[PDB]
C-alpha cells in the first residue's frame, strides 16, 4: 500500500524483499595494506556515474534524512561541542551511516528504536514498515560518489574491532560493503584498554595515514565491540592561494593569534540577514558542491547564529543568496576531531539502546557489549566594486551537495589551530 505517515517511501522494504557463515577477524597487528584513496575515489564516481534513476532519488532522500537527524542532535544539546574532542566539526552523513550500520545488525525493539532515531516511523508492526538497511547503506555510498563525482576527495573507512573469539556473521560485513568498500574487521583484546587503544591508533594511522587518537574513553573492559567510522575530506579552493604572511585571528576581544590565510577572488553567492545579523558566503567546489561560510556580524552572537544554522530554515536561505563580487580571506583549515554517538544521542537514550536488552544478533550470536561508537573526522581545505569578506574571527561552515541535498559536514571554527 501507499505510505502517508512519512514521505520516505524509497528507504523501506517493498513487497518482494519483505545457517550463516561466521569468522574471527584477523588480529589487528596482522599486516594490512594501506588504503588506496585514489583508487577508492574512482570507485565512488563510478558508483555515482552508473546510478539508476530510482537509486539517484533514494540518495537525495537519505541526504535529506541525514540533515534532519543533524538538526535534531543540535536541538537536544545545551552544549554540543563539549562532547566533541579536538576540532568542533560534525558529519551528519557519517552519524546517519553509523546508526544505519548498527540498525543493519539489529532486531526487534532495538531495530525499531534505532529506526526511530533515524527519523522514519511506522503505523504498524508489518515487515514492510521497517527500514531496508541495504537500500539505506547503498544510498549513502551514492551520496559519497555524488559529492566527488564532479577538486574533492572523500574517503570513508569503517573499523569493526571485536573481542578475541567473537564470531562476526558474514552477511553483516557483506552489508557494510554497501556503505563503503573499505571495511576493516579486526580482532582485538579488550582486557588492556590503554594498549588496546594504542593498537587501534597505530593500526588506523598506518592503514590511512590520518591521526585519530581515541583512547577508548567511554569503553570498559567487559566491552566486546568497537564500531568506528573514519572519514577524510580534502577540498580544493577554486582560485585561492595561500598567503606567505599570516594574519590575526581574534578568538576573543582581548587575544588574537597569527594564522595562515587563504586568499581568493571570484563571483560568489552572498547574503546578509539584517534581522538576525549574519552573512552567508558560498564558495563552490563544483557546481552542486560548495562551501557555506556563516559569519555573525558581531562575535557575541556566535551561539545564536549557530542556532539558526542547525535548523531546517538554514536550507531555505540557499535561495536568498545572490551573486556578488567578493574577495574572501579565511584561515587554512586542517582539522581533526572525534565524538561518540552515545554522547551525541544521550538525550535520545542511545546509550540505553546499546546496553539494555541489546539485540544485535544479526551482527553476531556472541554476546555484544558496546565499547564505543566513534566518528573520526579529518577535514582539510587546500589552495589552488568588490565586497571584502574576512574571517578573522570565529565563524561557522558547512559543506553541501545539491545532487543529493546532503550536508556532509557541519563545523565551528573558534580557533584555526589548537
Ligand atoms: C524490491 O527492491 C529490491 C531491492 O533489493 C528489488 O530487488 C531487485 O529486483 C531486480 C528486478 O528488477 C533484480 O534484477 C534481476 O536480477 C536477476 C538476477 O537474479 C536477473 O536475471 C534479472 O534479469 C534482473 O536483472 C535484482 O537482482 C534484485 N536485487 C535484489 C538485491 O533483490 C526488487 O525487484 C524490488 N521489488 C519491487 C516489487 O519493487
Image (cartoon, rainbow, N blue to C red):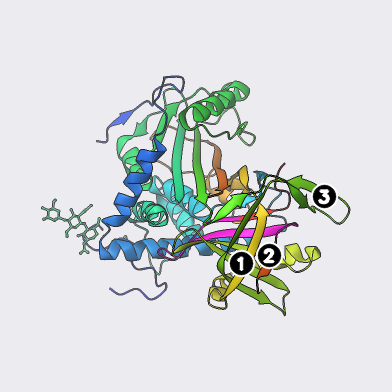
**C-alpha separation, residue under disc 2 versus residue under disc 3:** 18 Å
> Residue placed at 41% from the left, 53% from the top?
148
Q: Kindly check if marks 2 and 1 are in contact, taking CB atoms under 8 A apart as contact.
A: yes
Crowding at label 2, few (<14), some or many (≥20) Cα neighbours within 10 Å?
some
Q: Residue at x 53, y 56 (%)?
A: 239
> Which residues are drawn in magenta?
390-410
Q: Secondary structure at mark 3?
A: loop
Q: Residues within 10 Å of mark 1 (few under 14, many from 20)?
A: many
Q: Nearer the viewer, residue 287 or 370?
A: 287
Q: Quadrant of ligand 1?
A: bottom left
Which residue, given by chain and number where applicable, does mark 3 sit on? 256
- Compared with 254, 372 (above or below) is above
| Inter-mark Cα distance, 2 to 1 | 8 Å
- Residue 297, given in percent of the width and then of the height, sits at 75, 69
Across and down, in percent, residue 188 comes to: 49, 24
Snapshot quadrant of residue 196: top right
In this figure, which residue is indicated by the disc labeled 1? 281
Res. 263 image quadrant: bottom right
Residue most toward the right?
254
x and y percent of residue 56 in the render?
A: 32, 63
Q: Which secondary structure, mark 2?
A: strand
Q: Which residue is mark 2?
A: 389
Q: Secondary structure under badge 1? A: strand
What residue is drawn where x is 43% and y is 21%?
27
Point out the image quarter for the N terminus.
bottom left
**Is residue 383 among the parts visible in the rendering?**
yes
Q: Residue furthest front?
A: 385
Could you tell me how many numbered marks the image carries?
3
Amino acid at each position: 500500500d501507499r505510505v502517508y505517515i512519512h514521505p520516505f517511501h524509497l528507504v523501506i522494504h517493498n513487497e518482494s524483499t519483505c545457517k550463516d557463515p561466521t569468522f574471527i577477524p584477523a588480529p589487528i597487528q596482522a599486516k594490512t595494506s594501506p588504503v588506496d584513496e585514489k583508487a577508492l575515489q574512482d570507485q565512488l564516481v563510478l558508483v555515482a556515474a552508473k546510478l539508476d534513476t530510482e537509486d539517484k532519488l533514494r540518495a537525495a532522500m537519505v541526504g535529506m534524512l541525514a540533515n534532519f537527524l543533524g538538526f535534531r542532535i543540535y536541538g537536544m544539546h545545551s552544549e554540543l561541542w563539549g562532547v566533541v574532542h579536538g576540532a568542533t566539526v560534525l558529519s551528519p552523513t557519517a552519524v546517519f551511516g553509523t546508526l544505519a550500520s548498527l540498525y543493519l545488525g539489529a532486531l526487534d525493539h532495538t531495530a525499531d528504536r534505532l529506526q526511530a532515531i533515524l527519523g522514519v516511523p511506522w503505523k504498524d508492526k508489518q515487515c514492510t514498515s521497517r527500514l531496508d538497511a541495504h537500500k539505506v547503506l547503498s544510498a549513502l555510498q551514492a551520496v559519497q560518489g555524488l559529492l566527488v563525482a564532479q577538486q574533492l576527495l572523500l574517503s570513508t573507512v569503517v573499523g569493526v574491532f571485536t573481542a578475541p573469539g567473537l564470531h562476526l556473521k558474514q552477511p553483516f560485513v557483506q552489508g557494510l560493503a554497501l556503505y563503503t568498500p573499505v571495511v576493516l574487521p579486526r580482532s582485538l583484546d579488550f582486557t588492556e584498554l590503554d594498549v588496546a587503544a594504542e593498537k587501534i591508533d597505530r593500526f588506523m594511522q598506518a592503514v590511512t595515514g590520518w591521526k585519530t587518537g581515541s583512547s577508548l574513553m567511554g569503553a570498559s573492559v567487559d566491552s566486546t565491540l568497537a564500531f568506528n567510522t573514519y572519514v577524510h575530506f580534502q577540498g580544493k579552493m577554486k582560485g585561492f592561494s595561500l598567503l606567505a604572511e599570516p594574519q590575526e585571528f581574534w578568538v576573543d576581544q582581548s587575544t588574537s593569534v597569527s594564522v595562515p590565510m587563504l586568499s581568493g577572488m571570484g563571483t560568489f553567492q552572498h547574503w546578509s540577514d539584517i534581522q538576525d545579523q549574519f552573512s552567508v558566503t558560498q564558495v563552490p567546489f563544483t557546481e552542486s558542491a560548495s562551501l557555506l561560510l556563516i559569519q555573525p556580524h558581531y562575535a557575541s552572537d556566535l551561539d545564536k547564529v549557530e542556532g539558526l544554522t542547525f535548523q531546517q530554515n538554514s536550507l531555505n536561505w540557499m535561495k536568498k543568496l545572490s551573486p556578488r563580487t567578493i574577495h574572501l580571506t579565511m584561515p587554512q583549515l586542517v582539522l581533526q576531531g572525534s565524538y561518540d554517538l552515545q554522547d551525541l544521542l544521550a538525550q535520545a537514550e542511545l546509550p540505553a539502546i546499546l546496553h539494555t536488552e541489546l539485540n544485535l544478533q544479526k551482527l553476531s550470536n556472541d554476546r555484544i557489549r558496546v565499547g564505543e561508537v566513534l566518528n573520526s573526522i579529518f577535514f582539510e581545505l587546500e589552495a589552488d566594486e568588490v565586497l571584502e569578506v574576512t574571517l578573522n574571527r570565529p565563524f561557522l561552515f558547512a559543506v553541501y551537495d545539491q545532487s543529493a541535498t546532503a550536508l556532509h559536514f557541519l563545523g565551528r571554527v573558534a580557533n584555526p589551530l589548537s
